[PDB]
Image 1: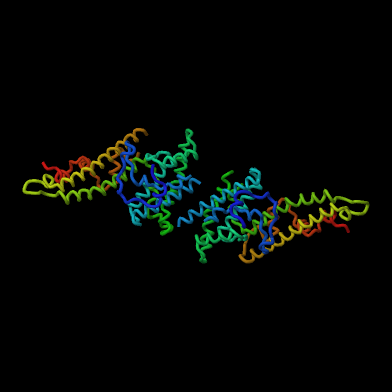
Image 2 (image 1 turned 90 degrees about the horizontal axis):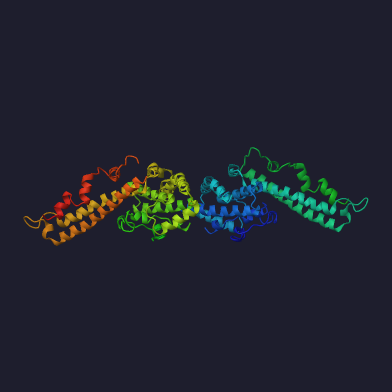
Length: 276
Length: 279
């Protein structure tokens, strides 16, 4: 949200920067959303025709940067990223985006001068997005997934939970492996390495900080899910609890094991990092 | 050479500039073609920029018609839509100035290979209803869904060779100019200056009125000669009710009298003889 041009010219590596729960404390915001290319949208009837051109250019630039981020590989990770960014464009257009920081406020203003602010303006916006989303997807996919699978409108908090889940299950093995390499087993016949070995202690503290961020992020996102769902009665067939989203998004997700992990009571964390 | 921005901001009045037979001598070019808005195409996704140029063109033709929703507006939309098509397909007969930049831009998009032309025609045929809609954007702002009843989409998206369409447009210009030029002539030349002599015999203002008429009708004759012969050579190098270029005038114009038309452009009609031939 804090720049306009530089973020249409390069992305950070994925997970280079963790979800941000501090800026607006009722939600956690992914780095990808912060970096969403909206240069033309910012520098912005015939105005509606001009809007569509500007949104197509931003979307193509976003989709191309995400390809380069995925090392030009055309695979599921790339397709998911396309879907997440497409979805956020949608919410920005529809006026239901949860970021609303910095230059996103300027874009919201631009849209208001184009569509109006009356009660039924938001209705116009939603309709215009429906009629445009296919083309935006095409535009993101131009440099190169399942179109109709993406175009399905889902509330933003649902989609950010899917994205969050994929980040968590990608981070978890790396973090556990780091722990293992420093802390596995014992320093003598009785005492775990964490009892006395400083590099193991360092490693456990680093893990603690990571899993504490994961827990706070799951707590904020999952509670946002519940309040959004209560406030606009988001009736979604497959999905009753926020855990349903993780179950459906993630291979071999075990929700009991998940709660154990983010609350530091799983077998691996206890074995490696709890002296007593 | 021509213009890029000016013609996307304003149009000259109708018939302020006559058809141009001098720039390319085997065809005559209408001022509307010369002014066709193509700013985005020139600076050139393609569908986006074409849609924008067409929307601007459509709104300008609406202004030219003084915001009147009538046949003259719909025919203009039809003529400009057709010209966009020949530009996209590579079959446009103007090909002056910025039109060549656009043709160059299209070649870098579609290619030049054996069937680049075939793909450009496919692209045009898939897009033409959409481009017509864009030209009607200005009307659709006001009438919403009822914009579709103002002009006939089906008539507009039928592909005719460009020379066919330009003959229809030419014919409509001719029958709009003729009553005016004849009235002008009549106001200086009607009747006699004495008991036996027609005014053209001795009245200089009438003699100059006849010269001026002669200048106009000579332009008309030359434009019809160039256009009708172009129709024939285009036809030979390649289709529904139209056999001769006169057939096109008959389809376009009310009760078109071919013999009278040939009399008029050849200065042997009754009105011209009466007004401008002394003996």
